[PDB]
Image (spheres, rainbow, N blue to C red):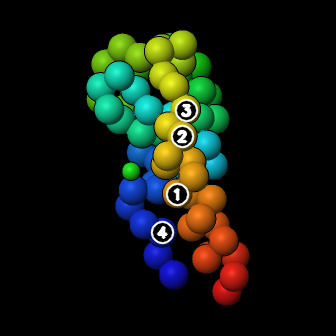
């Protein structure tokens, strides 16, 4: 019933809807990080600088989440 940790967003604390990855190699939900960077003014969870224009959509993980959604919504 639990959600796999690799699909969890550090911010929303739940399943990622569209995974983006930072140059540092960190993975967030696209919309969860967008609003969070607005609330803190381009600062991440650890207080370090981060802009939304510096992340890309992690494609392979996005594909993996879609597959997970199939097996989850099956139950
Ligand atoms: Cl992966």
Among numbered discs 3 and 1, the one appearing first in the sequence: 3
Question: Which residue is tagged 4?
Answer: 3
Q: Secondary structure at mark 4?
A: loop
Classify mark 4: residues with Cα within 10 Å, few (<14), some (14-19) or many (20+): few
Q: Any mark on residue 57, and which?
A: 3
Question: Which residue is tagged 2?
Answer: 59
Residue 49 image point, x, y percent: 36, 14
Spatial separation of the CA atoms under disc 1 and disc 2: 9 Å
Spatial separation of the CA atoms under disc 3 and disc 4: 21 Å
Question: Which residue is tagged 1?
Answer: 64
Contact between marks 3 and 1 (CB within 8 A): the answer is no
Residue 9 makes an appearance in the image: yes
Residue 47 makes an appearance in the image: no
Contact between marks 2 and 3 (CB within 8 A): the answer is yes
Q: Secondary structure at mark 1?
A: helix
| Front label number (2 vs 4) | 2
Among numbered discs 2 and 4, the one appearing first in the sequence: 4
């Amino acid at each position: 019933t639990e959600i796999p940790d690799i699909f969890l967003c550090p911010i929303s604390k739940t399943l990622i809807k569209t995974p983006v990855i930072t140059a540092q190699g960190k993975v967030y939900d696209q919309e969860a990080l967008s609003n969070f960077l607005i609330a803190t003014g381009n600062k991440d969870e650890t207080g370090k600088k981060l802009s939304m224009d510096d992340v890309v959509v992690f494609d392979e993980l996005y594909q993996q989440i879609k597959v997970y959604n199939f097996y989850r919504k099956r139950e």
